[PDB]
Image 1 (cartoon, protein in one colour):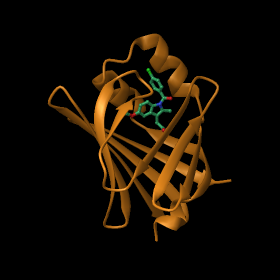
Image 2: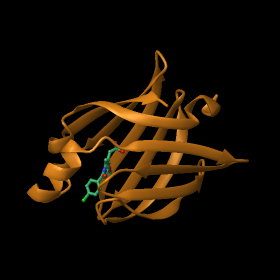
Image 3: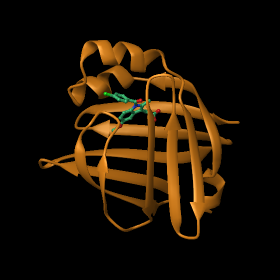
Image 4: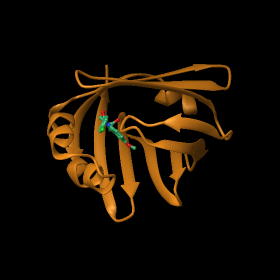
Amino acid sequence: MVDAFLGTWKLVDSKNFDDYMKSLGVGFATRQVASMTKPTTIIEKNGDILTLKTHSTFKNTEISFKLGVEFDETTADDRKVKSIVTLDGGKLVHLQKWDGQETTLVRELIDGKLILTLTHGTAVCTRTYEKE
Ligand SMILES: COc1ccc2c(c1)c(CC(=O)O)c(C)n2C(=O)c1ccc(Cl)cc1
Protein backbone atom coordinates (compact mmCIF):
# COMPACT_ATOMS: atom_id res chain seq x y z
CA MET A 1 0.00 0.00 0.00
CA VAL A 2 1.15 3.75 -0.21
CA ASP A 3 0.98 3.42 3.57
CA ALA A 4 4.29 1.54 3.70
CA PHE A 5 6.04 4.81 2.65
CA LEU A 6 4.72 6.69 5.67
CA GLY A 7 7.06 7.65 8.48
CA THR A 8 10.46 9.15 9.16
CA TRP A 9 13.44 8.24 7.01
CA LYS A 10 17.14 9.17 7.22
CA LEU A 11 19.68 9.20 4.38
CA VAL A 12 22.24 6.42 4.58
CA ASP A 13 23.71 6.24 1.03
CA SER A 14 23.96 8.48 -2.06
CA LYS A 15 25.23 7.83 -5.58
CA ASN A 16 25.75 10.55 -8.21
CA PHE A 17 23.88 13.36 -6.42
CA ASP A 18 26.57 15.83 -7.54
CA ASP A 19 25.96 14.86 -11.19
CA TYR A 20 22.19 15.30 -10.71
CA MET A 21 22.67 18.72 -9.07
CA LYS A 22 25.11 19.86 -11.81
CA SER A 23 22.50 18.83 -14.41
CA LEU A 24 20.03 21.29 -12.77
CA GLY A 25 22.65 24.11 -12.73
CA VAL A 26 23.23 24.11 -8.96
CA GLY A 27 26.38 26.10 -8.11
CA PHE A 28 29.51 24.39 -6.75
CA ALA A 29 29.22 25.86 -3.23
CA THR A 30 25.67 24.63 -2.83
CA ARG A 31 26.63 21.23 -4.25
CA GLN A 32 29.40 20.99 -1.67
CA VAL A 33 27.04 21.64 1.27
CA ALA A 34 24.13 19.66 -0.13
CA SER A 35 26.63 16.73 -0.77
CA MET A 36 27.55 16.43 2.98
CA THR A 37 23.95 16.73 4.29
CA LYS A 38 22.02 13.60 5.53
CA PRO A 39 18.42 14.81 5.34
CA THR A 40 15.42 13.40 7.14
CA THR A 41 12.33 12.74 4.95
CA ILE A 42 8.90 12.58 6.61
CA ILE A 43 5.92 11.23 4.71
CA GLU A 44 2.43 11.73 6.18
CA LYS A 45 -1.11 11.33 4.90
CA ASN A 46 -4.51 12.75 5.77
CA GLY A 47 -7.11 11.02 3.63
CA ASP A 48 -5.87 11.28 0.08
CA ILE A 49 -3.55 14.28 0.84
CA LEU A 50 0.09 13.28 1.26
CA THR A 51 2.70 15.62 2.79
CA LEU A 52 6.40 15.12 2.15
CA LYS A 53 8.84 17.06 4.30
CA THR A 54 12.58 17.03 4.02
CA HIS A 55 14.65 18.53 6.83
CA SER A 56 18.36 19.15 6.99
CA THR A 57 20.99 21.59 8.32
CA PHE A 58 21.02 23.22 4.89
CA LYS A 59 17.36 23.50 3.87
CA ASN A 60 13.81 22.49 4.81
CA THR A 61 11.13 21.67 2.20
CA GLU A 62 7.50 20.63 2.41
CA ILE A 63 4.92 19.82 -0.23
CA SER A 64 1.38 18.59 0.06
CA PHE A 65 -0.52 17.10 -2.82
CA LYS A 66 -3.28 14.73 -3.86
CA LEU A 67 -2.07 11.71 -5.79
CA GLY A 68 -2.76 12.15 -9.46
CA VAL A 69 -3.64 15.87 -9.28
CA GLU A 70 -1.16 18.43 -10.65
CA PHE A 71 0.20 21.16 -8.41
CA ASP A 72 2.53 24.10 -8.75
CA GLU A 73 5.81 23.61 -6.87
CA THR A 74 8.84 25.77 -6.01
CA THR A 75 11.63 23.20 -5.69
CA ALA A 76 14.42 23.10 -3.05
CA ASP A 77 16.76 24.56 -5.73
CA ASP A 78 14.27 27.37 -6.53
CA ARG A 79 12.79 26.12 -9.82
CA LYS A 80 9.11 26.94 -10.45
CA VAL A 81 7.61 23.77 -11.90
CA LYS A 82 4.36 22.00 -12.67
CA SER A 83 4.28 18.69 -10.73
CA ILE A 84 2.28 15.53 -10.26
CA VAL A 85 2.82 12.59 -7.92
CA THR A 86 1.33 9.24 -8.77
CA LEU A 87 1.63 5.63 -7.80
CA ASP A 88 3.04 3.50 -10.54
CA GLY A 89 4.12 -0.12 -10.08
CA GLY A 90 4.07 0.44 -6.33
CA LYS A 91 6.51 3.38 -6.65
CA LEU A 92 5.75 7.01 -5.80
CA VAL A 93 6.60 8.86 -8.94
CA HIS A 94 7.00 12.67 -8.69
CA LEU A 95 7.33 14.38 -12.08
CA GLN A 96 8.40 18.04 -12.32
CA LYS A 97 8.02 19.93 -15.60
CA TRP A 98 9.37 23.37 -16.46
CA ASP A 99 10.57 25.02 -19.67
CA GLY A 100 9.97 21.73 -21.60
CA GLN A 101 12.48 20.01 -19.22
CA GLU A 102 11.48 17.19 -16.86
CA THR A 103 12.85 15.49 -13.82
CA THR A 104 11.51 12.53 -11.91
CA LEU A 105 11.89 11.72 -8.22
CA VAL A 106 10.90 8.06 -7.84
CA ARG A 107 10.58 6.38 -4.43
CA GLU A 108 10.32 2.62 -3.94
CA LEU A 109 10.61 0.26 -0.99
CA ILE A 110 13.14 -2.61 -1.18
CA ASP A 111 13.95 -4.79 1.84
CA GLY A 112 12.50 -2.14 4.17
CA LYS A 113 14.65 0.70 2.70
CA LEU A 114 13.31 3.61 0.70
CA ILE A 115 15.22 4.11 -2.54
CA LEU A 116 14.92 7.53 -4.19
CA THR A 117 15.97 7.68 -7.86
CA LEU A 118 16.42 11.20 -9.27
CA THR A 119 16.62 11.47 -13.08
CA HIS A 120 17.25 14.61 -15.12
CA GLY A 121 18.19 13.88 -18.73
CA THR A 122 21.18 11.53 -18.53
CA ALA A 123 21.91 12.20 -14.84
CA VAL A 124 20.68 9.43 -12.51
CA CYS A 125 21.17 9.66 -8.74
CA THR A 126 20.22 6.94 -6.28
CA ARG A 127 19.71 7.76 -2.61
CA THR A 128 18.91 5.24 0.06
CA TYR A 129 16.99 6.10 3.22
CA GLU A 130 16.42 3.92 6.27
CA LYS A 131 13.49 4.03 8.62
CA GLU A 132 13.68 6.01 11.92
C1 LIG B 1 14.66 17.99 -7.82
O1 LIG B 1 15.40 17.18 -6.80
C2 LIG B 1 16.10 17.63 -5.66
C3 LIG B 1 16.38 18.99 -5.37
C4 LIG B 1 17.03 19.40 -4.20
C5 LIG B 1 17.45 18.43 -3.30
C6 LIG B 1 17.17 17.09 -3.57
C7 LIG B 1 16.54 16.70 -4.72
C8 LIG B 1 17.63 16.33 -2.45
C9 LIG B 1 17.53 14.84 -2.42
C10 LIG B 1 16.86 14.14 -1.24
O2 LIG B 1 15.67 14.45 -0.93
O3 LIG B 1 17.53 13.23 -0.68
C11 LIG B 1 18.17 17.18 -1.53
C12 LIG B 1 18.81 16.83 -0.23
N1 LIG B 1 18.09 18.51 -2.03
C13 LIG B 1 18.49 19.66 -1.32
O4 LIG B 1 18.44 19.73 -0.09
C14 LIG B 1 18.85 20.86 -2.13
C15 LIG B 1 18.31 22.09 -1.81
C16 LIG B 1 18.65 23.21 -2.54
C17 LIG B 1 19.53 23.09 -3.58
CL1 LIG B 1 19.96 24.50 -4.48
C18 LIG B 1 20.10 21.87 -3.90
C19 LIG B 1 19.78 20.76 -3.16
